[PDB]
Amino acid sequence: GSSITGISPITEYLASLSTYNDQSITFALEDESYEIYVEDLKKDEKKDKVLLSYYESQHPSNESGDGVDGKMLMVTLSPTKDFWLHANNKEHSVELHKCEKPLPDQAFFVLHNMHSNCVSFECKTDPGVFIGVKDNHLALIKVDSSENLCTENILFKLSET
View 1: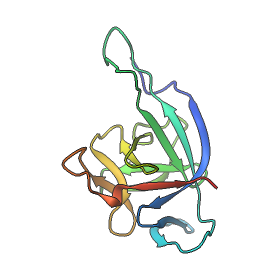
View 2: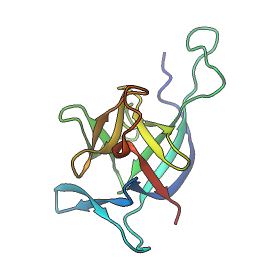
View 3: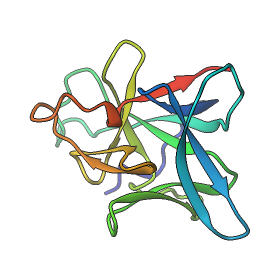
View 4: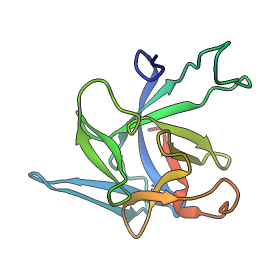
């Protein structure tokens, strides 16, 4: 009856999101405001790191799914404590929100490989949508798996410091 809840975390580590344009995503947290903007890098300066975690989805056999030996690995990004990255379809943008322990489908983002070390975050509840820097902040970039392969804005980089 359910295949979303009841899972377990694979691995957790710190990693800052960096655009393919050699830029890092700055998460400014005010008294109660949430401002996000991408800043350009120059030297090896330890910027804001986001707590990323991996999650594996288990599909039922002999019923529905028909896997091909390669379950999609989801990922959760948390630059703060209880506030996680949630994809708001309202304005097609990602905002930090504090929800209960049972994280919704809008929390787990299916990670996908793009380049040698580049990665992209895909929406599990809304396939076809990938996280990415829109104008100058994080937003939901609607990109296809072929009709739009040339998209540097949807290219993320992880730094293991």
